[PDB]
Amino acid sequence: LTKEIISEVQRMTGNDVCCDCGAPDPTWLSTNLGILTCIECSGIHRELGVHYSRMQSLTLDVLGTSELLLAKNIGNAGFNEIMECCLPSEDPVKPNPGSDMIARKDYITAKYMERRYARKKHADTAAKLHSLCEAVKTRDIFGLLQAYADGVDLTEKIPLANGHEPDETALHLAVRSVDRTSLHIVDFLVQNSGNLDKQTGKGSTALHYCCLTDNAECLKLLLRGKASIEIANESGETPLDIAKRLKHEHCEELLTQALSGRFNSHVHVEYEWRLL
Ligand SMILES: [Zn+2]
């Protein structure tokens, strides 16, 4: 299963060269970005910290299918189309397979931390948030990626007109609007948001939302991201309380596992991998 998704990921057009230096056959995956790098560039990404890039060997390490949602939907070509859109013209800034560590470090820092080569699309804040909102509603992963390239705050409230509760973020919206074909939209937000605990005007966190609709797959992504299970909504309920009350067994079992400090390592989720 995971092996079949990995071979698919490796065969994606553009995934045959390291995202950052061109080295052939990259095998290191940045799970929150859906891209593949050579081992050398991989070493620099590790230094950036999990708030920027979470590395794992695609062919050597054991992975939960949930960690391949982004790899399956993004890929080097698509990612670089946005992140290297403004790479210098007559100034060969991008490292090549023979480049030293100092050179990869300077480029990788500028590319990912500074976003020096990304296409800055939107005319700031207001626009950025609106595009993020639309990207989620249309389930467009590259639209989410662009918002992230523009440096949008993924945890900020979005200009949503008919939200379920006031002050929803893109994560609240994503959780209640994605399905088996679009879990990766929720995943992108979970792996690139520093705070998965934002609350609606009624104190609801994305976890609460998951329990209200018995969305166990989104719930699994959130727990993997260590969203806090003890935050209560304005009525005093925690997500576990909601799950019990509505009798949503799967959600109850998952939250109870987490509550007892025994939650899953390699998190698998039901998704339309389309590997037939
Ligand atoms: Zn490389």
Image: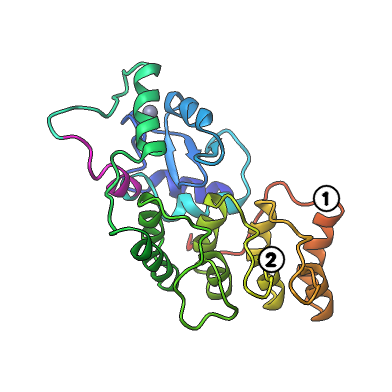
Amino acid type indicated by mark 2? Leu
Q: What secondary structure is marked by label 2?
A: helix
Ligand 1 lies in quarter:
top left
Looking at marks 2 and 1 on the same chain, the residue that comes earlier in the sequence is marked by 2
Of all residues shown, which one is farthest toward the left?
A: 90
Residue 220 horizontal/vertical position (percent): 68, 60
Residue 211 included in the magenta stretch of the image = no
First to last magenta residue range: 79-88
Q: Which residue is mark 1?
A: 262
Q: Are marks 2 and 1 in contact (CB under 8 Å)?
A: no
Kindly report the distance in space between the C-alpha atoms of the residues bearing marks 2 and 1: 18 Å
Residue 81 included in the magenta stretch of the image = yes
Whether residue 1 is visible here, answered yes or no, is no
Residue 226 horizontal/vertical position (percent): 69, 51
Residue 131 horizontal/vertical position (percent): 36, 66
Of all residues shown, which one is farthest toward the bottom?
A: 162
Query: Which of the two discs, 2 and 1, sits closer to the camera?
Result: 2
What residue is shown at x 48% (from left), y 63% (from top)? 274
